[PDB]
Image (cartoon, rainbow, N blue to C red; front, side, top):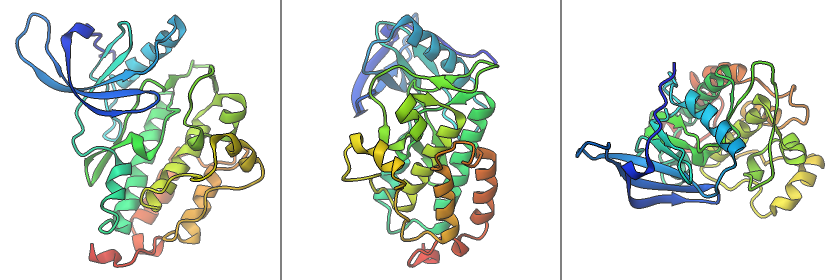
Amino acid sequence: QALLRILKETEFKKIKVLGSGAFGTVYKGLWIPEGEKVKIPVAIKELREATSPKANKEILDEAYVMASVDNPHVCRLLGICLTSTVQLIMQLMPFGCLLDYVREHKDNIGSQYLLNWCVQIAKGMNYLEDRRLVHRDLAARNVLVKTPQHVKITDFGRAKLLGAEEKEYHAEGGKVPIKWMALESILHRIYTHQSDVWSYGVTVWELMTFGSKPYDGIPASEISSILEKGERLPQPPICTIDVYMIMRKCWMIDADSRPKFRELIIEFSKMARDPQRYLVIQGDERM
């Protein structure tokens, strides 16, 4: 139940950069246990910014849950460095993220695969919700491919554990993935399990469009007022009215009108067992 290992930042050798963003940077690296000569390849995700004692406490709480995940669709935290800068130690994911996968396999991805990825992502989110984690970071670039049949949700220190009494999380200022965020989050910096549902919706949009960019063209600044105007992301060309109407429910203004992750698992599960009733892909069953 409590498995989290806290390691010395001196036990890691960075080897190459796998990626970098605003929020931090992922290294291909090497763990070398102190007192040991064995070297073991890890991914090292270290946060761009330094953190307050409050920030660390929250990352530390979330980290203890992450280090103990049962679920096939969430990446387990291997270890953590609470040194100068925080570093999450994750297992290497050589296929990379689902966002990349769908962009360069666009022509061989069938309705069956898309709908299965949605079920798996929802299962991982539903499980995180049971562990009381609000993910705050769900996007296609944060779903990793273990095999094309098997995807996993990963975290970069942004998830937040909720006290047994709490239903919200109110966040500080800073950089945010504003085009994946529920409107409450953008307006009031409040996050809940239901704002996670909003992001699931955008992530499913990302997949159904084979890697399209959300609100591409609009600056972050307008997003809030465009959503207030009623605009949402457009219906993807392969979506039936049934799939799209679900995305639209994920982007409802009242977060209690959005579906639950357990309902999302049920809907996409039935769709997943008759893919061609719901997605209209050209050459679909020829892939």
